[PDB]
């Protein structure tokens, strides 16, 4: 019915600013100006991402949070920078961190309020707030730490409404840092408690996805962000578009998540870089094409959701779809009946005549988590860089206590390869 | 047979007479019983005031079906009204204090931000 | 001296109606009432013009009694000698004797006394009624009981219309008849039975009427009645009084039921044929074909014979015709009884209804005979009855008015006795 | 001496409205107006069916009862609609049923009184009330149910007077309606206790009379009702006509019914559809011509009554009649002497130069009852549509208790094939 | 007399919309409101309330917990058809779980509806029952419906309720949690509802592929076909009829037992635009391929059949159509319902939507049958349910609105019972 978008922390901000300028140009929106596109649909559900202001004009429900200038004035001065409402930019000023605690306790809580006082403004403004979605990094601090807090402070203020996040789960290849496992594990914990669904964009997949499969030698944060931006348009489509379904996003949740421990979706995409239907599915359900670094093979699908894009006959889709869950019949749990559903919206993405996107609650996502607690226990082992948090005011055992919660999550997933 | 006839009486408008033909040869209505007519009269008021106070039998058995229904209805109405509403204060009490079993488990990892930042203004 | 008529019940009334008419034609009373002792026997010279019968008519529906106060003779009776009951008898003794009878019974009984009140030395009652039929059996019986109380000695003379299959009965007839004739027998002195079968039969053989009416029947019964009374409204020796009735026909208290036989019933249009002979009319009398209870007495025995001749007739003949009736027939007089024959001639020529079917005659015989074979009728009723009551057939409608189941038993039980008494008079 | 006519329930009302306009036109009566006919008799016993009012005019002693508008205004607006006294129409308004209990308890007893208050106002008006005669269906409710009740409530208020009915015992042909057996069996019970005579018009026969012997392909309720209408004029004839008999109707009862258990007459007719005398009787005593679905062959006649119509010699009738009970001599019980009587009125019916009608107390009527208790016990078997009554306030065992009374009736008839 | 429509929930509404449309095309009401059909100053009155001096307004109320769909009505023509009030909308959605609509989110609106339906039955002298159209699976559709109906049962004691459920099928997209929703409502709702016309979405979609030849059948595609089945079931009391019959009789026939029994729906001739025999259309009805709930009754037994013909038919024909739909077909009528096969003809031609996919026909059958095999649907739901609940699958989202764990048990417990009752009706 209507959703606000929080977008915090260098990585978060980057992603979101690409998100925005993809969908904005899908609905047909100027840098500021309103509609320009000989389509019509667009404006049906434009409502959901776009609180509108003075005259024509269209402005995205968006709160931009960060603990240091730069990366905001990177947006402001660039793509669709004139778009976001000016006092919707919540500057940090201070140190950032690249350290959870800073963002979740000392330098973060410093701000939080000032953000929360503007999320309040957009949400309390909304005709019927559906929920918030948030974008950020899991490793490093001002997105992972402030975020996990924004949400922890968003629920409580709206237990009512549901929580949605795109969280970029990081890796050794492609990092700002040593310390992330720490930051990741400290969030993954926070995530599993206060959100309802999270999309795991694994940077590791994204990388493998640009070098194993995309000719690109050293990937920027650019061609690479590029992938998320496309996947995110994909995931959201049928909230913001047609009259196929309607997708309360609550509906999306209460249909995708069997078990309260907010299970993390690994997304996927169809065509890529910067298409026959059979050749679309077999690709969208290929591991080498997942947005999270797993191989949905070691482990099964709890529930799946696939959403296709472009004027193609769904005669062929139902049929291709049921056909994947046949040549792969064993890897869809058989205790949840029709646990793969499909939808068709026929308004193409960027270039791209065909396309699909894929959302998957898969126990194989365990492989991801295990591999971040892997380099975690290897570090917190002999209490490595820990004195970076110790001193900012954290307890020794808040790490074990997080490490151990996460370990559980791994072993509930590992459980649901049941019978 | 050759007759021998003796004449009795010779009126003005008639004659009678005996004629033997062959000598023969050989050698309380009481009133009391009308009490037997009010003996009917009171066997016939029985007959009736029976199969009358016997159709007065089936009579207010009508008062009965026309009741075991109406009474049967208010037993359903005024029974599954609180078989609803008392499963719906049952509901409120269950979430209305579970949305608050969510809140107090938060305000706790919260009153914990303060009690370990008022420990960072004590540390290094 | 005086002689009241009571006609109870549709049949009784209709019969009564068409024999008062014949009394009137015989004595010359134009309907209004006036004629231009002797025949005082039956009429009470009321007011200074009129002649009013000594009659009372009761029925439990109007309807029939209504036709009297509508058709001429409408001026013949006193308004009060015609009593009518509103609710019908419904064709069962039970009703008339108890339920519906009770109600009117005290009215009648009063009115008949009003009538016998202007009578210095009243003689008896003629009672005309139906054997089967609702009030006819029921009321009659009741009337008669109470008569027996109110009038001690005074003879009662019943003229029963014994019923037959064709001239339409009712299923339940048999009951009714057995019922009354029980209760009514110890209270009545002499009873002229009239078999409807017989009459109808005579109207077919003799009159040649294919479909004989009541009004057709009645006319012929009208005559038999006139001829039996005759003797006392004219005064012409024999049966000149009521005692003298059972005095001559029944030797046995058991109400005996004399056989009626009429003489020359011949259809007008055969009128101006020959006048029949003094001998011949007699000779018809001793004929089954001309009887008045369907039976035969060439099988039973005679216990008193009475010949009632009317008209121009001299004894000399009667005698010398009887002679040859004895010489040419089945005498059969029983064991211990002369060989009867009390013969009365009433010089009065026998008048017949003008638009009637029979013709003016010269001389008519009458024949009142008490035979043991008259109980062949007694039995034919009884069988019908026996075989219904075997199954309580209709019993209930009577138990329904409020009778006893055993008043049916205790009445059959009587017929069985009488059926045996009659047969026990044999040699 | 004088009779009032109750006519209740859709079927009841249909039948009676045909009855009325047949007899009315026999006596010579206008829609309202009085006499028009060069006959004279007519008016003799016009008394018996016609309480008279204002000026000329002739109005039938009739009470029209039903639990729903329609079918009355079907009469009001149609044949002799202007005839019946306006506040002699007792509407229902409510649901009807097609369900005894509705009419005999809940929706019925709701009215009863207001009908009973008008029957009172006709009977109490009558010079000398002979009794009531009523028409209705035995399957279905507002006739069979309210009816059986009217009468149960009429006796009691007049034990005195006798009860007469025309009851149409319903069939599997000519209507589906899974329940009637129930309604029928629930009435037959009622009937056997509180009426004195009932004519059983078996719809099953009626059908067959129109199809087995008539060629009438699309059988209306219409033609088929035309059969009853004729049978009824015949049955009644010598109450309402001549001076042959006079027919107290009590007389008719106390002559036709040997056994208190109100024995039901199956009627019969002579010529039909919409004649020699021999050819009349041999037809009036044919099974293929009976108004009730029997074959008076399996079972004998207890008592018979036949009434003829038209200027024909009864010389030939006495003779034809005695001649049936001779070539069929065995099938007239011999423990009841002259148990078949005849009557002749010479004023023809509708068209029809000759005609006869036949009333028969026949133990073969058992074949009818058995066959309703046949589909009854087949249903009440496993307590079928019974909850339709249960809920309206009736007891389970009131069905067994009726089923069992009826079964007795069958076995008292079956008994009176004795010796 | 009068007959209110309640359409709750997306499916219910969208079905409702395209069969009020059909009602309107049948009775000749131009969207505008007014009908050139002569007055309304009854009959066409069963479903419409002749409002003001021009218009015809349905006796309808539409509830749903999102606007969106309800919104489509007050936007597309017919926008002038309803009163503004009779369209109620809920702002916050149902979220696809019984728990929500029955307790959390419903509580809120429920009082509004309940009020407005009463406003509507207030101008109704002798209102008859309710038609309730809703989804089996689906958020408000199960949840709200259920609540509505409980409360209806209280506010309107007798007045029957007639539910039209849309039983759900895998392809025409369900939702994981569907199974729960359906088992849940049908439990609570069952003791409060009188007769329920199930419609299997599968069936319909299936018929649109076999017969209509539409590769990708829309809701708007389906609804149209359901629009008709509904019209033909109501029909009877919608147009007058004469030469035939209302539900209430068809109702007494279909449901022999407490348990709300769920009649099968079959339509007659679905033939795509761009005349079949009276016999043949019938023959179609007794065909798995043409049914309304995917299953088969050449495996179950019948406990009542109802055939509803519409249009150019004569009984002489239906007679032989049926008789032969027995002589050599899938017979099976059970131990104790001698009847089955009620039959009426609603002469009014089977008017189909103008740009629709089906064509104007001459005559159409409708067949409403209560079979024990209809419980083969009952089970196929249950298994899906059993095997999810085995692990608490999604339970929590319901315990989260505030339900009991055991209201899931205590409702399965009923299906098991009903699944047994049905099977227990066997010979
Ligand atoms: C006199 C009133 C009546 O018209 C009598 C029948 C029923 N209706 C009228 C309309 C009617 C009839 N048939 C219809 C079919 C569809 C819609 C309407 C009808 C009616 C007829 O054909 O008139 C021309 C008719 C009906 C039946 C009918 C005959 C009939 O007209 C001849 N059958 C006698 C019954 C029936 O159920 C039965 O008892 O079989 C023994 C019969 O079963 C068979 C195979 O005959 C049958 C015939 C099709 C089958 C199924 C439905 N039942 C209902 C009753 C029965 C029918 C006539 C009321
Ligand atoms: N001879 C003759 N017999 C008649 C006459 N009228 C009736 N009956 C017979 O009498 C018997 C019937 O008796 P009813 O007089 O009709 O019965 P009731 O109770 O006296 O008169 P109701 O009260 O009208 O029934 C049958 O046997 C008839 O055959 C008649 O006028 N003449
Ligand atoms: N036959 C038919 N079924 C439908 C239609 N729309 C939805 N459904 C079915 O109904 C069920 C979904 O019901 P919903 O209306 O979506 O549930 P709801 O909560 O009541 O309505 P929402 O508040 O919109 O969710 C599924 O089984 C669908 O297949 C329709 O238009 N026609
Ligand atoms: C954001 O909008 C979406 C919203 C929803 C769904 C979805 O995935 C296709 C979305 O796209 C990403 C959805 C999902 C999943 C299911 O579980 C597999 C389901 O049964 C059902 C659905 C959607 N409904 C259907 O597929 C029935 S047509 C409803 C909720
Ligand atoms: N793919 C994607 N990941 C990013 C981007 N920027 C940073 N990251 C990842 O997110 C993690 C840290 O993010 P960073 O924003 O510096 O932490 P912050 O200070 O909380 O904003 C690292 O592990 C990076 O690999 C981005 O541009 N796109
Ligand atoms: N012949 C006659 N019988 C009818 C008529 N209408 C219905 N019936 C039969 O009687 C039964 C029910 O009659 P109905 O009047 O509708 O019941 P009600 O609800 O009591 O009025 C049906 O099963 C038919 O068999 C009628 O028109 N005439
Ligand atoms: Mg009498
Ligand atoms: Mg919903």
Image (tube, coloured by chain):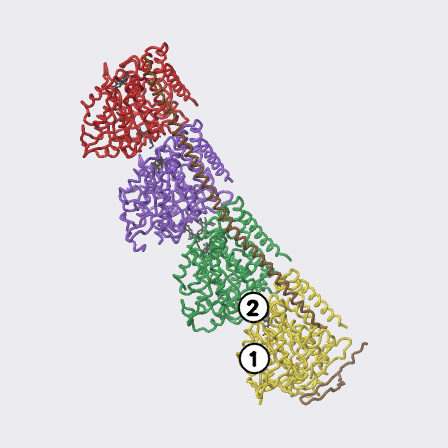
Chain colours: A red, B brown, C yellow, D green, E purple
Mark 2 packing: few (<14 Cα in 10 Å), some, or many (20+)?
A: some
* Foreground residue among E289 and E57: E57
Work out whether residue E133 can be spotted.
Answer: yes
Mark 1 packing: few (<14 Cα in 10 Å), some, or many (20+)?
A: few
The reply, left or right, for residue A89 in relation to residue C73 is: left
| On screen, residue D348 above or below C44 | above
Chain assignment, label 1: C
Same chain for the residues at labels 1 and 2, yes or no? no
Which of the two marks, 1 or 2, is nearer to us in this view? 1
| On screen, residue E135 above or below B63 | above
Work out whether residue D288 can be spotted.
Answer: no
* Foreground residue among E1 and A399: A399
Q: Is mark 2 within 8 Å of ligand 2?
A: no
- For residue D397, which numbered disc appears in the image? none
| On screen, residue B60 above or below E293 | below
Image mark count = 2
Q: Tag 2's secondary structure? A: helix
The answer to whether mark 1 and mark 2 are in CB contact below 8 A is no
Label 1 sits on residue = C79
The reply, left or right, for residue D190 in relation to residue B27 is: left
- Quarter of the N terminus of chain A within the rendering: top left
Q: Tag 1's secondary structure? A: helix
Label 1, label 2: how far apart the Cα atoms are: 40 Å
Q: Is mark 1 within 8 Å of ligand 2?
A: no
The image quadrant where one finds ligand 4 is: top left
Which residue is at a point 71% across and 89% down the rendered structure image?
B10
- For residue D318, which numbered disc appears in the image? 2
The percent position of residue C392, horizontal first and vertical second, equals: 64, 61
């Amino acid at each position: 019915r209507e959703i606000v978008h929080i977008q915090a922390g260098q990585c978060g901000n980057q992603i979101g600013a690409k998100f925005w300028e993809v969908i904005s140009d899908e609905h047909g929106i100027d840098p500021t100006g309103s509609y320009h596109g000989d389509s019509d649909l667009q404006l049906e559900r434009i409502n959901v991402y776009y609180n509108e202001a003075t005259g024509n004009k269209y402005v995205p429900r968006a709160i931009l949070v960060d603990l240091e200038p730069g990366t905001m004035d990177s947006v402001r001065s660039g793509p669709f920078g004139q778009i976001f409402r000016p006092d919707n930019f919540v500057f940090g000023q201070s140190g950032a961190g690249n350290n959870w605690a800073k963002g979740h306790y000392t330098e973060g809580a410093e701000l939080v309020d000032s953000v929360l006082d503007v999320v309040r403004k957009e949400s309390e403004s909304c005709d019927c707030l559906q929920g918030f979605q948030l974008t950020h990094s899991l490793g490093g601090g001002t997105g992972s730490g402030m975020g996990t807090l924004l949400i922890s402070k968003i629920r409580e203020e709206y237990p009512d409404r549901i929580m949605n996040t795109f969280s970029v789960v990081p890796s050794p290849k492609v990092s700002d840092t040593v310390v992330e496992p720490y930051n990741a594990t400290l969030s993954v914990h926070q995530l599993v408690e206060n959100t309802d669904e999270t999309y795991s964009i694994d940077n590791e997949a994204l990388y493998d996805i640009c070098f194993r499969t995309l000719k690109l030698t050293t990937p920027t944060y650019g061609d690479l962000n590029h992938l998320v931006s496309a996947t995110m348009s994909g995931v959201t489509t049928c909230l913001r578009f047609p009259g196929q379904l309607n997708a309360d996003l609550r509906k999306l949740a209460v249909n995708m998540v069997p078990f309260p421990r907010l299970h993390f979706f690994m997304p996927g995409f169809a065509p890529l870089t910067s298409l026959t239907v059979p050749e679309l599915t077999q690709q969208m359900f290929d591991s080498k094409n997942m947005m999270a670094a797993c191989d949905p093979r070691h482990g099964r699908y709890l529930t799946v959701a696939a959403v296709f894009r472009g004027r193609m006959s769904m005669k062929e889709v139902d049929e291709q779809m049921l056909n994947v869950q046949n040549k792969n019949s064993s890897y869809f749990v058989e205790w949840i009946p029709n646990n793969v559903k499909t939808a068709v919206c026929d308004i193409p993405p960027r270039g791209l005549k065909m396309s699909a996107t894929f959302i998957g609650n898969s126990t194989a996502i365990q492989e991801l988590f295990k591999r971040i607690s892997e380099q975690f226990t290897a570090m917190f082992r002999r209490k490595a860089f820990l004195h970076w948090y110790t001193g900012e005011g954290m307890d020794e055992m808040e790490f074990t206590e997080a490490e151990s919660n996460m370990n559980d999550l791994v072993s509930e997933y590992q459980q649901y390869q049941d019978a | 047979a050759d007759m021998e006839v003796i004449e009795l009486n010779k009126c003005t408008s008639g004659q009678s007479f005996e004629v033997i033909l062959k000598p023969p040869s050989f050698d309380p209505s009481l009133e009391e019983i009308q009490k037997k007519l009010e003996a009917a009269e009171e066997r016939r008021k029985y007959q009736e005031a029976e199969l009358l106070k016997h159709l007065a039998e089936k009579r207010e058995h009508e008062r009965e079906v026309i009741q075991k229904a109406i009474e049967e209805n208010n037993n359903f109405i005024k029974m599954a009204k609180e078989k609803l509403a008392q499963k719906m204060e049952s509901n409120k009490e269950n979430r209305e204090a579970h949305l608050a079993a969510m809140l107090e488990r938060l305000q706790e990892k919260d009153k914990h931000a303060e009690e370990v930042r008022k420990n960072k203004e004590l540390k290094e | 001296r005086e002689c009241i008529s009571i006609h109870v019940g549709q049949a009784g009334v209709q019969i009564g109606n068409a024999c008062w008419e014949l009394y009137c034609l015989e004595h010359g009373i134009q309907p209004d009432g006036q004629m231009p002792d002797s025949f005082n026997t039956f009429f009470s010279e009321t007011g200074a013009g009129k002649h009013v019968p000594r009659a009372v008519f009761v029925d439990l529906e109007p309807t029939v009694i209504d036709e009297v106060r509508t058709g001429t003779y409408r001026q013949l009776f006193h308004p009060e000698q015609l009593i009518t009951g509103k609710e019908d008898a419904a064709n069962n003794y039970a009703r008339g004797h108890y339920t519906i009878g009770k109600e009117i019974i005290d009215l009648v009984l009063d009115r008949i006394r009003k009538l016998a009140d202007q009578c210095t030395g009243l003689q008896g009652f003629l009672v005309f009624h139906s054997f089967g039929g609702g009030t006819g059996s029921g009321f009659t019986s009741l009337l008669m009981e109470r008569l027996s109380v109110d009038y001690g000695k005074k003879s009662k003379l019943e003229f029963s219309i014994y019923p037959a299959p064709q001239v339409s009965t009712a299923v339940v007839e048999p009951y009714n008849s057995i019922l009354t004739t029980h209760t009514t027998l110890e209270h009545s002195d002499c009873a002229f039975m009239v078999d409807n079968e017989a009459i109808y039969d005579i109207c077919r053989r003799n009159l040649d009427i294919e479909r004989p009416t009541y009004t057709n029947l009645n006319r012929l019964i009208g005559q038999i009645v006139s001829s039996i009374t005759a003797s006392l409204r004219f005064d012409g020796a024999l049966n000149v009084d009521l005692t003298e009735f059972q005095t001559n026909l029944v030797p046995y208290p058991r109400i005996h039921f004399p056989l009626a036989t009429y003489a020359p019933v011949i259809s007008a249009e055969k009128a101006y044929h020959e006048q029949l002979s003094v001998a011949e009319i007699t000779n018809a009398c001793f004929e089954p074909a001309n009887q008045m209870v369907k039976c035969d007495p060439r099988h039973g025995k005679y216990m008193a014979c009475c010949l009632l001749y009317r008209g121009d007739v001299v004894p000399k003949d009667v005698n010398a015709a009887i002679a040859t009736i004895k010489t040419k027939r089945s005498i059969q007089f029983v064991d211990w009884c002369p060989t009867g024959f009390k013969v009365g001639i009433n010089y009065q020529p026998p008048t017949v209804v003008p638009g009637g079917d029979l013709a003016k005659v010269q001389r008519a015989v009458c024949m009142l005979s008490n035979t043991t074979a008259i109980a062949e009728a007694w039995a034919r009723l009884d069988h019908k009855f026996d075989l219904m009551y075997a199954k309580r057939a209709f019993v209930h409608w009577y138990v329904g008015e409020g009778m006893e189941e055993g008043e049916f038993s205790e009445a059959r039980e009587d017929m069985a006795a009488l059926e045996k008494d009659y047969e026990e008079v044999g040699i």
